[PDB]
Image: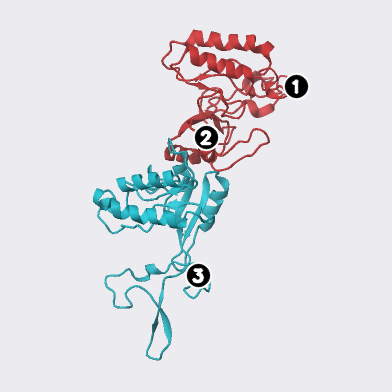
Chain colours: A cyan, B red
Amino acid sequence: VDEANIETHGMVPMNRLTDDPRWLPAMSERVTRMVQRDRNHPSVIIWSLGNESGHGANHDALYRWIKSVDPSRPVQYEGGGADTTATDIICPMYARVDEDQPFPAVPKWSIKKWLSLPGETRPLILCEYAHAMGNSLGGFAKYWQAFRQYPRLQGGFVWDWVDQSLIKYDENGNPWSAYGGDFGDTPNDRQFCMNGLVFADRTPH
Amino acid sequence: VDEANIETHGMVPMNRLTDDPRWLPAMSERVTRMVQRDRNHPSVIIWSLGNESGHGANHDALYRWIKSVDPSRPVQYEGGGADTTATDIICPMYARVDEDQPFPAVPKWSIKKWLSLPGETRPLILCEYAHAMGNSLGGFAKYWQAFRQYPRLQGGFVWDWVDQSLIKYDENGNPWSAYGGDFGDTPNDRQFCMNGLVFADRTPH
């Protein structure tokens, strides 16, 4: 799944830029250059419009642009609540199997519910699920139970492959794994950089 | 829900008569006379084509006839596997909440699965569910949990209201409740006549 380099996650609201005409040139270049570059790979199955940037008109536009230019692949976008008109696939992040999380504005349904909501005909693939933050993946089996049982639950992507930790050294010259804040970077989000299935040295959790 | 007086349950296969042109006159009269009779009631919400008679061409025809003549109500039919083209409502019998029962030919999906099957857009209402045979209704809460959670699960009908037992008398002139076989009727299906929420005397289980 090949994602455009666009994430405006820290904006308030998230789509402050992606629903703003003036940034559409910037965004368009990011998307269009990506597509032109990777157009010919066979491994690339799905185009993604980016990540967590809310849902704005610029997404709708760029969705359509890709569909126009490369009709051979499907386009995915989770921002806006997984199921806006700028996605071919219902694609949500950390939606639970049997539990609805009715957030104001952008409710996050259970994946089983989501499929059946009046009008939903698309496939559902979990953009991000199962948050592997250290000692985790509890209940992982539930997802795979569901994936096998339901036809339109077509899998998903575990978050994520490898811990984003950095090596620092102690006074003896020994190396150790550093997380947010350990370089004097402040504010930071501490251990949240490490959510891998494998360690940074590619040994496995 | 007003049902036409048609059930060919004991046929082999069940639709032996209902897919046979020559019985279409008989069937049509049953349906059409019913509709003409009860057309004007406000309590009548749904027309039903009958019960457990498989799925044959005669159902398709009669479905259409009703739709033509009384477009103000919806038409329901469970035979054939709850979701044939002769029904406006996915309407199944004893489909379990979270358990698929993949029967040859006419699989009976879990109701949660059923809603989401590629192409299903209709509402789902359980023709018959929760079989109240004596000391029963175990797990009833699961249905109502589901009904409240999913938008297209719109309830169902419990099977059933009152025990079909008959009074017989002993040598002292005392009355007692009789079930299949107690009148010398053989073969019979014994206690299966009693599946009520209330007793035949309308006291409650």
Q: Which chain's residue wears label 2?
A: B
Q: Pointer 3: residues within 10 angstroms few (<14), some, or many (20+)?
A: some
Mark 3 belongs to which amino acid? Val
Classify residue A11 by image quadrant. bottom left
Q: In the depicted view, which residue is nearer to us: B185 or B175?
A: B185
Q: Residue placed at 49% from the left, 38% from the top?
A: B143
| Picture layout, residue A88 above or below residue A167 | above
Callout 3: SS: loop
Q: Residue placed at 24% from the left, 51% from the top?
A: A22
Kindly check if marks 1 and 3 are in contact, taking CB atoms under 8 A apart as contact.
no
Q: Which residue is mark 3?
A: A198
Distance, label 2 to label 3, CA atoms, is: 40 Å
Q: Which residue is mark 1?
A: B186
Residue A130, visible in the rendered structure: yes
Q: Which residue is mark 2?
A: B119
Discs 1/3, front? 3
Mark 2 belongs to which amino acid? Gly
Q: How many marks?
A: 3
Task: Please state the horizontal and vertical placement of residue B102, each as a whole percent of the image.
Answer: 64, 39
Q: In the depicted view, which residue is nearer to us: B204 or B175?
A: B204
Distance, label 1 to label 3, CA atoms, is: 69 Å
| Disc 1 with disc 3 on a shared chain | no
Distance, label 1 to label 2, CA atoms, is: 46 Å
Q: Which chain's residue wears label 1?
A: B
Q: In the depicted view, which residue is nearer to us: A62 or B82?
A: A62
Classify residue A7 by image quadrant. bottom left
Task: Please state the horizontal and vertical placement of residue A81, each as a whole percent of the image.
Answer: 37, 47
Callout 1: SS: loop
Left or right: residue B5 versus residue A68 is right
| Disc 1 with disc 2 on a shared chain | yes
Task: Please state the horizontal and vertical placement of residue A5, each as a whole percent of the image.
Answer: 37, 59
Mark 1 belongs to which amino acid? Thr
